Amino acid sequence: EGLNLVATALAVGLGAIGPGVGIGIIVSGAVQAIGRNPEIENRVVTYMFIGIAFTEALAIFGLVIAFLIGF
Amino acid sequence: REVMANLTARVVGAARRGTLLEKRETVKSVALLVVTPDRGLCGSLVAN
C-alpha cells in the first residue's frame, strides 16, 4: 500500500520536532550571552555553530531516511 | 571598602569595566577637589 508515504512524512515530521526546539534554544542562549558580554562574541559564536550543527545532524538524518523511504 | 574588594574582584573584564571604574587611556582633562576651612586663623593649614 501507500504506508511508505506515512514513513516519508514521519521521518521529516517527527525528525524536525527535536532540532526545531534545539536550534531555538542555542541561538537564544548565544544572543543573551552576546548581549551581556559583547567582547566574548567572536568566541561564543564558534561554540554556537559547532553545536548548532550537531542538532541538525539528526534532522539531516531524518531527511536522509525521508528520501531513502521514497526510493 | 571590603564590598569594593569583593565586588571589583568579580568584575575583572575590561569590556564590563566601564562607567566610573573605567581606567581611561590618554587622559586629557583632570578635575580636583579641595576642602578648606570656612574661617581663617587656622595657621599654615590653609596655605599648605
Image: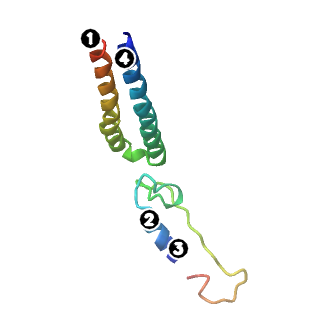
Q: Nearer the viewer, mark 1 or mark 3?
A: 1
Quick check: marks 2 and 4 in contact, CB under 8 Å? no
Residue A27 lies, with reference to residue B1, above or below; the image says: above
**Quick check: A48 above or below B24?**
above
Q: Chain of mark 4?
A: A
Determine the residue positioned at 30% across, 16% down: A69
Marks 3 and 4 belong to one chain? no
Residue A10 lies in quadrant: top left
Q: Which mark is residue B10?
A: 2
Q: Which mark is residue A8?
A: 4
Q: Position of residue A35 (x, y in %)?
A: 48, 44
The x and y percentages for residue A36 are 48, 48
Amino acid tagged 4: Thr
Q: Chain of mark 2?
A: B
Residue type, mark 2 in image: Arg
Secondary structure beneath dot 2 equals helix
